[PDB]
Amino acid sequence: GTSKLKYVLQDARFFLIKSNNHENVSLAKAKGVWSVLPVNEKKLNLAFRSARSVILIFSVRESGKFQGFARLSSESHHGGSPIHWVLPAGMSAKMLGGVFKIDWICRRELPFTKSAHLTNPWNEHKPVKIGRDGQEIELECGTQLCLLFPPDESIDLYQVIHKM
Ligand SMILES: CNc1ncnc2c1ncn2[C@@H]1O[C@H](CO)[C@@H](O)[C@H]1O
Image (cartoon, rainbow, N blue to C red; front, top):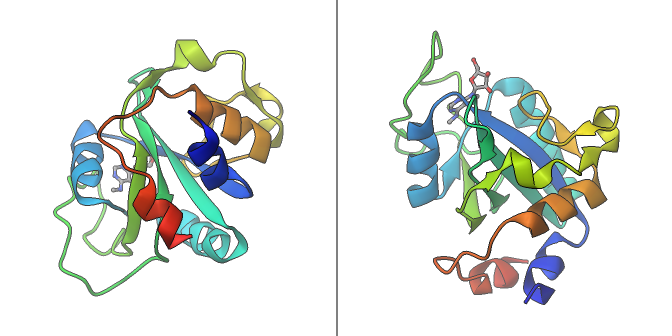
């Protein structure tokens, strides 16, 4: 059912995350970590204190799809073992050195075709698939977008529910 997911998403903030490459999303899905640029890292740490849950919704550039969504379980961390990210054009192993711990809620894909009815009021009521990396998605739009994803049998929400 959706009671568990709705509980997780009650009073959540939502952010569109754009990856240039599939490799880092595969790494992140397995390991439960993500890193962003400094501009977005500040917003995510502010949000992590502001919010009961902070949800990252992933889309690989040019894929036409979202690849899943995850909940921050930590503020950005520096100083851990390096994550061997596939670094894009001219980015440093310290340009995204801040590491967020994340718990995946859904690792299954959602094609942009299934979310075409949803617009983000905080991006001029454009369809939610449209957005800059780190674009914040308004509460109800983000909630409905997350509810569109198919159930993921690899995920157990018990840990997340306990972390809250
Ligand atoms: C793990 N962290 C990341 N992995 C892959 N692409 C990223 C990324 N963080 C930011 N990007 C993207 O790479 C570009 C930064 O130069 C932007 O277009 C972002 O959308």
